[PDB]
Image: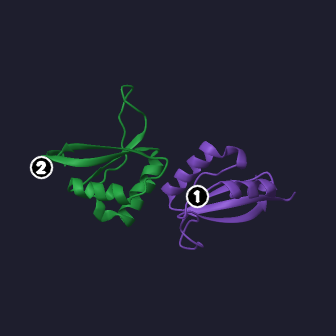
Chain colours: A purple, B green
Amino acid sequence: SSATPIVQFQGESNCLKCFRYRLNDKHRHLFDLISSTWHWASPKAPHKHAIVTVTYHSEEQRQQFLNVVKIPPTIRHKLGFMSMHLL
Amino acid sequence: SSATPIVQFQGESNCLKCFRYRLNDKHRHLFDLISSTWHWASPKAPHKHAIVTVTYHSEEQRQQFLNVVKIPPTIRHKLGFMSMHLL
């Protein structure tokens, strides 16, 4: 509706980029969009890890992704939402 | 000995870079030198993977490395030697 379900992955950039490659290789059907690697700039930031945002068509698809995909321990993930208007 | 034991790792470069940092953080004293990622240039190349070279002080250290380190699934490895002179 007004909100798109997302998972944000956080970690060191190369490990994250490796993970992104893996998702694109094997799990393209379990998510919608996936971003390039990014971070929060400047010392005014919540953390300084690299970040990849992955979006889903629905909360069901996000849950199916989380049930299937093995997230490496060195990559943290957080669920949330962003305005669908932003895509 | 005039030959240095090596392990060559092959895969997607961000995966190899992630692996390299993991090696340096958790297994630094089970290998000697570690290269940057490289590949074979031009159309003649035997493959198109990126590559990392890891050297060892001795065959005993290499075996201990292989006994202990869990090599991630994006990455293939081969064992061999290179002239010590080249280091």
Quickly name the residue at label 2. B1
Name the chain under label 1: A
Judging depth in this view, the residue of A44 and A79 nearest the camera is A79
The residue shown at (72%, 59%) is A6
Q: Position of residue B61 (x, y in %)?
A: 25, 58
Q: Give the crowd class for mark 2: few <14, some 14-19, many >=20 residues within 10 Å.
A: few
Q: Position of residue B87 (x, y in %)?
A: 19, 49
Question: Label 1 amino acid?
Answer: Trp
- Confirm or deny contact between disc 2 and disc 1 (CB under 8 A): no
Q: Is residue B33 visible?
A: no
Residue at the outermost top position: B44
The residue shown at (37%, 30%) is B46
Judging depth in this view, the residue of B7 and A21 nearest the camera is B7
Question: Label 2 amino acid?
Answer: Ser
Q: Secondary structure at mark 1?
A: loop
Name the chain under label 2: B
Evaluate whether label 2 is on the same chain as label 1.
no
Quickly name the residue at label 1. A38
The residue shown at (23%, 57%) is B60
Q: Of tags 2 and 1, which is closer to the observer? A: 2
Q: Position of residue A31 (x, y in %)?
A: 71, 50
Q: Is residue A57 visible?
A: yes
In-image side of A81 versus A68 (left or right): right
